[PDB]
Structure formats: structure tokens, C-alpha cells
Amino acid sequence: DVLDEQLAGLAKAHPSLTLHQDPVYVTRADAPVAGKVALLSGGGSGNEPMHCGYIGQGMLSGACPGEIFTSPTPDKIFECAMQVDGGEGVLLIIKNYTGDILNFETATELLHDSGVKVTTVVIDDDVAVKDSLYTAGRRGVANTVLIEKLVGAAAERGDSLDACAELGRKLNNQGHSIGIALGACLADNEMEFGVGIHGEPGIDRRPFSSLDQTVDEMFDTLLVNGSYHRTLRFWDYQQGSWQEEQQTKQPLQSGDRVIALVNNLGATPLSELYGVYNRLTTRCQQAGLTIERNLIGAYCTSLDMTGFSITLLKVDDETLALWDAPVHTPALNWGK
Amino acid sequence: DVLDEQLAGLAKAHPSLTLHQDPVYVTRADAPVAGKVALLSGGGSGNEPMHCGYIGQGMLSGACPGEIFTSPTPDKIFECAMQVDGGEGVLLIIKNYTGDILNFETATELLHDSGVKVTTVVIDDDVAVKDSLYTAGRRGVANTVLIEKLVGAAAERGDSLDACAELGRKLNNQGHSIGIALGLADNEMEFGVGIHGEPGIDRRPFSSLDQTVDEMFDTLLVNGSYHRTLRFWDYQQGSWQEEQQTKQPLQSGDRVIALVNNLGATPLSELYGVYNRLTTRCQQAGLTIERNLIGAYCTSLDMTGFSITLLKVDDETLALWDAPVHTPALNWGK
């Protein structure tokens, strides 16, 4: 009942979104938007504003909330995708959770069989742990926000479904996150190091010394666990089947230009995030990493968890242009 | 050196801001902005993004933070005002705490004597408690954000200092806030809490979110009417002037802006729940919500709780609301 109230609250607060019922999902009020690739994502509730706060021009066409930390069911994704298709196809952005993979796969196959041009982007940016509670491989966390915006800008520009997907998968290979918690959504002055956004265990528990030192070791870990080989699955709409792809991520390195997301996991004071950004900037400078753009705030939460995550995404000039492009969502608003 | 690191983080993240040192204050990087009334505010650290996240075009020209929950010293205010004045004068916005009142007063008077056209707007929107720990009269809370935007838009349009101050004062007489905290024992809430952790009306039980909103909404109505004396700087006379003023409660036919504000550690999903119930009570009482803001706009560090603010508006102030704003915490328009 409280999930419904929250969803009705979102709809009343934002007349530019439409709350659908039977089954439940959220789209832009003007969807289907003709002439442009539609972008869709979704996942459990409890990560707000992800994803419902990112519905609007220059970002998501729609999103399908599940129950708390629980993948939406495939009827929500299918119907939402049908709702948002504007004749150019629908790109599904999927965080690497087993329930999310399972459910978005089911929908995608069926959408293709229903005549909708579709393909998929998997997000696996969390560098901490391989094969956590609900994940085969690495977890999909805050970098999803950054990809949704960048791919959103590409779609809004009028790039083909293939160009959008390719951009998303490439950005996926160059984004790197890690989170810490000081309290659950742990002993005294002890942090869960490398925590995930649905309450999952991290690398371990360790002492929390200071914000600066916590940041140093988060930063170091981005570098140390940066290298990553794995197989991902994507929908080939030409062949009309799942295709296994082997991709390797390279660590960030001196010379790289980055977007930095310093993200509140739920209950960290905002002053402290600037303290985190301050230390992050110093460590990037010393490594030869140039932070070109940043976001600081509550973008990918875990209910009321006390902690924060850091995300660094390699970018170029073309990507910065996509960053700087307009976006109009509840949670991210700039440009004309 | 946490506070210093934090402010350094802010200057690094926002090249559109200048962090000044000796004394410490923040301004727009293009301050002084000639041709417009400058807006300045300040207060203790710990209410972020209030105030430094409100520095930019269409809102504040600068801000003066203090220590944790502690008024900025008058040197910061004096120096910030001087830095931001663009020849059209400086409007100081002040939340009603005794240390804020004194230090702002000290700076306002000295500024006038140093040749700066200056006046003041005092914020006392918290309906909960008269004479809290650090306040004579009513506490100044999240309506500050709404006034700072609306007055910010008026300044940016080119309204005079007098017109800007008069608008600020009128809005302060039409805006109504209350907050609650859950962190207190099991399922208990501090009702009518402040943003520095001052006591509320009492401790009471927390039954449900909807029930909490209902009682917050009722209190906005019940404590709506308020008469008190406020002091402002008359720059024509060169003196403090007292004015007896009265707020009317919210009533049927009123149109309002709503701010559902995170006091620090409330999940965003829950604020939409609050907003849902708030609209229901508003519509039931014949109040129209025209615009809304939901999120973390006036915090109290990592407090578990939230506040509701309702500000009566008309067509003219809606136009000021819709006007561009470009700050770290509020960004829209061309």
C-alpha cells in the first residue's frame, strides 16, 4: 500500500510523467515520442531517484519499478517498451542482477517477436565483488545514471538504436564504481567496504579511520580492480537471438579524462560528499586523471543506508558534448 | 580540518563559485554583478545545501557560512556584502536565530556607514515553537529556500532593493513550515523540531506517515495566525525600524508552493509518500498546490525526519518561481 502512495505522489508531483496501472510503470507524459530511439530501464524500488527520477527528455522514456530491491516483472517491461516505442526501437538498460537479467531477457525476446526493434545494455560497474548475493559477475550500481544520461542525449539527438547501444556498452566498459557503508539501510567505527545497493556484503568489514583515508582506499581499489574480463549477453535484433560477447575493461590511467559521481547511499550529510569530492580531486590530480564534470548528491540510493559511492567514467570530447546536452527529468535538469 | 576540506570540495566542484579566504565566504565567480540588487544570506554549517548551494544567477550572489549550527561572524558578512554589491545595493536575508540576528545587524549597520545601500528580510516560518533554544519569536527554516529563489528572480529581473525587500517580507508573512524527527525511543517522534536539533512541541508517537502529515498539516493551519515585531534596516533614515506584523493562516482559495524537505536521512521514496498525502489534505482544505520541490533543500546534518512548507502565491510570484535559476542545488530555465 505504501509503494502505491509513493508512486501516486511521484505522479502528482510531476505532471510530465504518466503513472500506468494494470500493470504498473511510468513513462514520459508525451510518450510514444515519434522519431527517436526510446530508452527504458527499471529495477527494484529503494534506489530512488533511480530510475523513475530519470524519466524525461534527454534521458529515459520510461521505467519499471519492481518491489523493494526486486526486479520488475516482465509484463511491466514489455508493456512499458510497447508504450514508449516511437518507431525507431527501444533500448533496454539493465543492471547486472540475476532477477533483472532474467526478467529483461524474457521481455526483450517477446518484444522482438511482437515486431518491436529492441536491444540491450548491461551495466556492471561495481568493482568490489564478483558473484555477490544476487549477481552473476559484477553489480550494476551508480554508473547506470551516467550511462542513462549520455545514451539519453545520443537518443534525443537522433542516433540509431545501434549507435545508442554501442555507445552504452562502450561507456559500460570504461566506468568504475565502489561503495562503502557505515550503517545498514558493523561494529563501532567499522565500515562495510565495497557494499552494494541492495544491502549485499562487500569485500569485508574494516576500520573507518577518516573520510580522507576511506576515499584513498576506495580510489586505490578503482585502480586495482579496474581490469575485468567477462562474457556479457546482448540481443541481436538482426539474427533475433542472444549473442555472447567477450569484453575486457581497462583500468583508468594517467592521461584519462573522467566524469566523477559522488553518490549518497542514503543518509550521508551533503557537506561530507564535498569532503569526499575534495579528496577525490587530489587523488585524480596525482594520478593524471582529469575530472571534467561531476555530480554530487543522492543519485543512486539504498533506502536510508549511511555511506556513499564513487564512480569514475572515462570520457572524450564527443562524450562531454553528450554530457552537456539538455536534460529535463525530476532528478537531473539542465540546458534549454 | 573537515569544514575547510568541505568548502574546498565545493569550490573545486563548482567553478562558478569563488571561495574567499581570510575571511571565509562564498560568492558567484562573477561577483560583483553590476546592475542588479545583490542577495546575501548565511548561517551555521549543517543545513546544506542551504546556503552555499543557492549561490548563482537568479538566486544568491554570495553566502557566509559559520561553524556547525553557528552564526557566521560579522566580518564574513561585511566582507561578502562588499564583494557582491554591484551598485544597486545588497539585500541581506536572515533566519531568525539570536546569533544570526546580532551578527547580521552588526554587519548591516557598519555596511550602511561604509556607503553600501542595504536592507534586510527576516525569516520566521517555523510554526512549531515560540522562543526555542536559539530564537526569540519563531525559528527560520525551509521557507528561506523559497524566498531566496523568488526574491532572487526579482533581483535578476532588475527590481529595486526596496521592491525586493518588500517582496521578501510579504512572502515571509505567507509561508508556513513545520518539521518532525524520528532520530527518541521506539516509534516515537519529536514533533515540531528545528533544524539545529532544538526541541519541538513534544515527543509523540509515530503511527504512520499519513497520520504524521495530517498532524503536520493541521498544525500549519492551527498555528497559522501570528503577530510579532520584526526589525529591518531603514536605509533612508540610517536606522533600525520596528514593524508590528501579522500572518494570516492558510485558507480555502489559497494557491501555494509546497516544499517537502528532507531533514537528512529520509529515503526519497518516503517524501513522495508525504507529498501524496499532503496534496490530499491540500485539495480537501481547498488549497491548490501550483508548484512543488521535493528533496534535501534545508537539512540538519543526518537527521531522520522531514519538514513541510507551504507558501501562498499568486500569478506574479508564480512567474518569479518559473524564472531561470542556475545554482548547485536548483537549476532551470534558459
Image (cartoon, coloured by chain):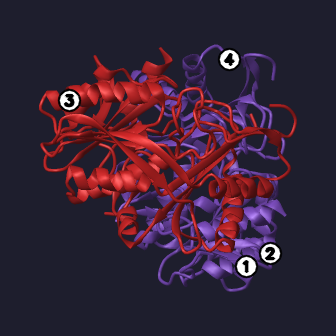
Chain colours: A purple, B red
Mark 2 and 3 residues: CB-CB less than 8 Å, in contact? no
Question: CA gap, disc 4 to disc 2?
Answer: 44 Å
Name the spot of residue B200 as percent of width and height, x first.
69, 37
Name the residue beneath numbered marker 2: A75
Question: CA gap, disc 1 to disc 2?
Answer: 6 Å
Classed neighbour count for the residue bearing mark 4: other residues with Cα under 10 Å, few (<14), some (14–19), many (≥20): some
Question: CA gap, disc 4 to disc 1?
Answer: 46 Å
Name the residue beneath numbered marker 4: A208
Name the residue beneath numbered marker 3: B111
Location of residue B247 with respect to B83 vertically, above or below:
below
Along the line of sight, the residue nearer the viewer: B133 or A332 = B133
Classed neighbour count for the residue bearing mark 1: other residues with Cα under 10 Å, few (<14), some (14–19), many (≥20): some
Name the spot of residue B316 as percent of width and height, x first.
35, 69
Secondary structure beneath dot 4 equals loop
Q: Amino acid at mark 2?
A: Asp
Q: Is residue A292 visible?
A: no
Which mark is in front, 4 or 2? 4
